[PDB]
Amino acid sequence: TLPDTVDWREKGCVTEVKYQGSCGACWAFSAVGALEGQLKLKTGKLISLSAQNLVDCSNEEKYGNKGCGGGYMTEAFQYIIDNGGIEADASYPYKAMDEKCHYNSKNRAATCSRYIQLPFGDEDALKEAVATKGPVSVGIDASHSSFFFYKSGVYDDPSCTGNVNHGVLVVGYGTLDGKDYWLVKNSWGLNFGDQGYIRMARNNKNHCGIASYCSYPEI
Ligand SMILES: *C(=N)C1(NC(=O)[C@@H]2C[C@@H](S(=O)(=O)c3ccc(OCC(F)(F)F)cc3C(F)(F)F)CN2C(=O)C2(C)CC2)CC1
Image 1 (cartoon, rainbow, N blue to C red):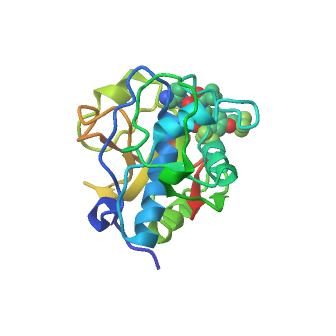
Image 2: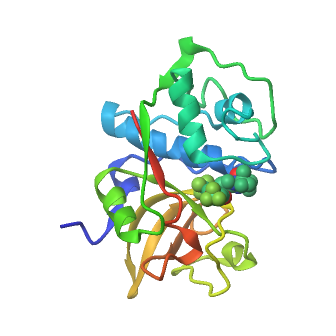
């Protein structure tokens, strides 16, 4: 059986909310967020990892990522795997611009061996992964102005579609005033949503495509 409510923030597995600025780096923050969760669960240390390392060093056709022009969480993991590591944010800080890759293996802060993809649109599979594995990288349709008007409750705008466009991180789930939600960490800083988080409708026919492209890394 699975718990009714999960919140990885309570287990110390979620770093501070970051601010992506005008660089289309949502995919990089989503990936490092998922990897940060796994690092904490394995080593016991919570460390912010370098979204900038991903933005600078995976901007090539091998991966299909485009730096500040967008990218894919799975390809970010693949880069980390191929590269034999990723730096911490401390040593490779976020600049919100495309820069020349300057990865240094002496500052390796985490590694990745493989990544897992969940079945397309399966919110039950996502619930199990969030419950038992940790934070999960997801794509959502975050193109509706209502997404940025949200302050509280459970975001459930009927105009949302399954055509996804932003990467974010699911750090938990539960039920708020009778409405099932996924607890989503964004990368728009602490002024977005509820302290950087939005609760998005769960079990409502894969709303905003939240369970369409789920993945998480394995250290
Ligand atoms: C964040 N600042 C930005 N968004 C961005 O980088 C997004 C993130 C992913 S996605 O989640 O939108 C996405 C899109 C399409 C996918 O597959 C469709 C297929 F292959 F089935 F046809 C998968 C994903 C997912 F897996 F979830 F990542 C990509 N993306 C993009 O902007 C891209 C590079 C244009 C697609 C920049 C706003």
